[PDB]
Image (cartoon, rainbow, N blue to C red; front, side):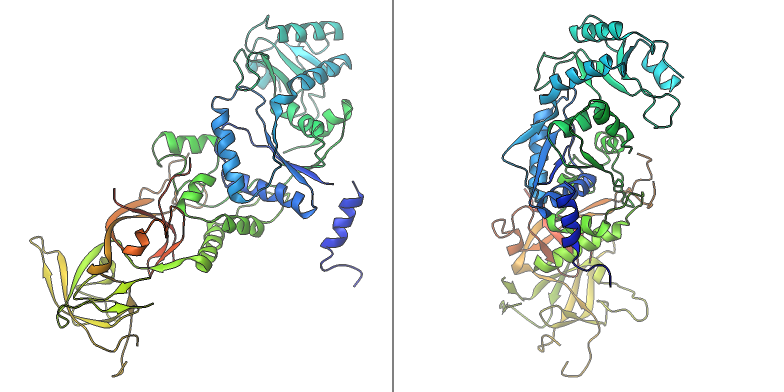
Amino acid sequence: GSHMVNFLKQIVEEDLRTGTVITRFPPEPNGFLHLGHAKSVCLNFGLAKAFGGRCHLRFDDTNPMKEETRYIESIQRDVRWLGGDWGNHLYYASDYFQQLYDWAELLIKKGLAFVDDDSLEEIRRKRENSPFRERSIEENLDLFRRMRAGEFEEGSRVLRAKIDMTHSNMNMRDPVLYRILKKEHPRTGNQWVIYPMYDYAHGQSDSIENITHSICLHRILYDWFQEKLEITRTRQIEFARLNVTYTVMSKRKLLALVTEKWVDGWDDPRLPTLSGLRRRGVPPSALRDFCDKVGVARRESTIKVEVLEKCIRDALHVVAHRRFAIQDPIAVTITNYGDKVETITARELHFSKKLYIDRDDFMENPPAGYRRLAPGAEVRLKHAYWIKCVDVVKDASGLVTELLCTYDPQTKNPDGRKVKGAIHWLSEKDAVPAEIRIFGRLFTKPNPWRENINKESLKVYKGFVERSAADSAAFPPQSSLQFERLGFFTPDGSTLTLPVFNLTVAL
């Protein structure tokens, strides 16, 4: 004793007294969200919900971003999909452009900011002092003012906080506050020609917004700005970026993967974007569950994809619908059945003279001790009878193209006895042409855009699907099918002709 249990309640009281809570999810509107953002989303929305508070949805559009509105839509989509609830209200860092500017003037007035004439080269080198650090307040302030006025040109001058070049912040060696960029803003138009850098704008945005718990790496700087400003303080909580084996999430590597056509679009199922995961057929709950099983941690680790796959598989398993599919068809004729077409309940499922099995389930010269079909051998057809293969017919190339099989009335079982293996199958009467896409891990090794990329990450088959599986009203573009003894599949869609299905996950 002297402790705990569902003393979630007590610590709820410590935070409650040590302060309603207000978090923010603040993506930049310059790119589709990925799995990492899911971790952030669960944390921020999660935390506000737990305390009956509010989580602001903020776009960090602190400089001109090309297709800002596209990303605003996409982000709202993905956050709703994940299950986050912001207000009815959208927040924008660009809304703070003036206040930010005013506060920057305050820094120069306190002798805590100066204008550096040295280049981006000279700066990324000398990080010792700028040659301009000891500029007077009057001169600094005037120079900044003219920077805003648009008198000097891109990169010629820059405004920097005046901290310690020595002190290993590490990013506390005179961080850049304002860069001069002569380009128009989606939202601010032509009103600004200098813009604030992420570090300068981030905590001040938090402050303006009365964010109580900011969840995001170093917060000496964040605290520094708030301290010296001296404005509403906001508690900065920092955790470790998400890392998953066989997976990359770097802006650069991802952009390469798309642009270089390694994958097909940002919503490709092999990609760890929320769009791609949604299209792969992963359900949002699997993701929420995954982000819970990853856990908080200040120290940087790496979760094995098997944890992800288990989350999505466990989720799919609860809500999938059993349906039959053949990816690499091979024909079976039942030699002792004749015509007539018997119904089976196991959804409409028939049994007839003409079936299909999957090629991987037959073998002409089987290893010793081999479940599954082979000449002379017998298998159980799931939800049906046992077939024995006697005779095979091959094409001109010697390729097996039809199996001749007797069956045996005595369905789900053994009358003898016997048994062995069971396989999936499809009656011709029930089959409809389909494109079955089998997706692998994007990469081949756990710790790689470093092209050690799975060249076999996508194999496409022209096969068959049980007719109700292509119902489209019954199974719309991200519903859950379990194609028996084949995997968890969703019908393909898009997250902005043959029926197409994606392998969402094995087993």
